[PDB]
Length: 182
Image 1 (spheres, rainbow, N blue to C red):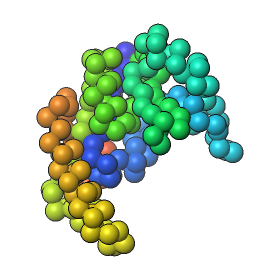
Image 2: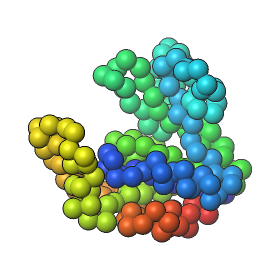
Image 3: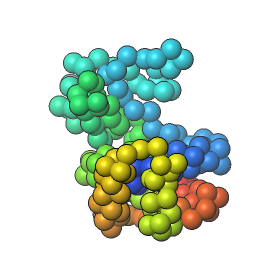
Image 4: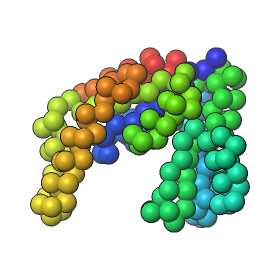
């Protein structure tokens, strides 16, 4: 039976390079393919990039409890979320599953699938995360202040998760996640 790992963390702690590393290290890792009600962009493939469904069918899925989590996107322009059945089927086949979601999505998945392992990718320090949020200083002071406030709130949540991986170094963050997945 494959492990299901839900990866989340602060907005902008470094999740997507980590995801790429994981998919290279585990040849058959199944990266959860979200359902969405937006239309496909050219180059997106149904079943690979997203499962493209219509709003009515997406509402049916909500009502039948077939989503582990879902959210309104861009204030309700459309919806996206994680389908339960492919995750469960992949796991029953013995293939490991990774789901990457924001913190609200991870909280939702722990309710709908408690056997999933939730992991919070934490920064090695406050100053490391603050430095990245300031960045090249292209944003206004109000925008940066809001980002720092948001980060402190999100960091307060790391206790809600099954595991904390500290992103000290890409190779060892990725290594710890590999150990969790296989």
